[PDB]
Image 1 (cartoon, rainbow over the protein chains, first blue to last red):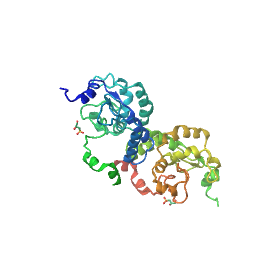
Image 2 (cartoon, rainbow over the protein chains, first blue to last red; image 1 turned 120 degrees about the vertical axis):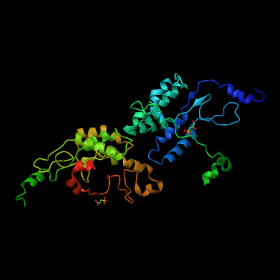
Image 3 (tube, rainbow over the protein chains, first blue to last red; image 1 turned 90 degrees about the vertical axis):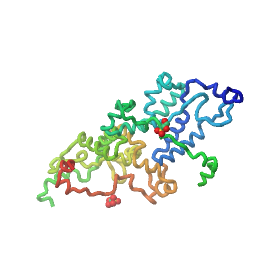
Image 4 (tube, rainbow over the protein chains, first blue to last red; image 1 turned 90 degrees about the horizontal axis):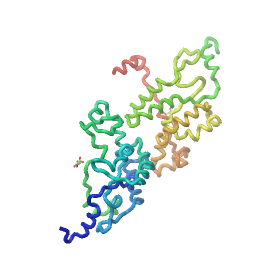
Length: 186
Length: 186
Ligand SMILES: O=S(=O)(O)C[C@@H](O)CO
Ligand SMILES: O=S(=O)(O)C[C@@H](O)CO
């Protein structure tokens, strides 16, 4: 029952069972920075790009939250990582709302920024394109059905072209015990 | 002087103290292939591109030579390596025939292919652009006068943005003793 839990149920009732939106901000300002730092150590470009996101993306306090911070708009939302799979945007964004499995909505203005600003930058630069291009012929057959590698064979499937990395647990205790001033001083 | 050497002097007289031409075919057919193999092992891409040059470039027998083969047009000529310094072409090709030091002439039809088909592929891709981009600030002072690194400070000058490599002596004896079928067979 909801006795004593008016705040959490107020937040949850507003979002429970809505269709999530595609938020473009992280991808947008990540791309904006990465575009200007090509050639530099990758993690240095990355850090610069996250600083650009930190400075420019919308900040949020979810209405009624005791916690501050989101990484996209109100409601249910997801965010984008074109460094992985931006070569799919052209084929896939059109029918995200209609996807039988796990549909998402996207505002026309977000589709416009995505296809005019973001996706054109990542052409020839995504991880997925690189992997598909260089896969040895002896391996292609069990990996991808098609020449662009947009369709898995579902025999020996690669899984690195839909995520950045395996799961991860950062050292949260270190951040709260020291704070980032002290880590930065190190 | 010229007794007994009619052949070499016929050849040499036709070209002595003539103005060398820019020939573009090596660059053109090199670029044409490198454009299609991005992401692959560099020396594999390089070999595909050299095969494209071998299949498509004009072959020549200099008139009256006993030796077959040039890598450019009749007369005195040079060829192009946009992989090094293609970011200079916009600024330098204009002033080439009137360059105080080491002038070169270029057919306007070759110059158009150069500046419309070749040079644009190499934007953001050249060695020189990469070096200039990443050089630590502590070191730019003595290396480059300008932000784009097109002018040496002539204090501590890098020399790798105007040549592919140091001098080199290939093992010619091995080529003539074995042939490339037997080397390919190894
Ligand atoms: O270990 S991973 O392959 O990164 C993910 C798995 O733990 C969750 O699906
Ligand atoms: O050794 S290098 O610096 O490649 C060239 C020098 O031999 C002068 O041509």
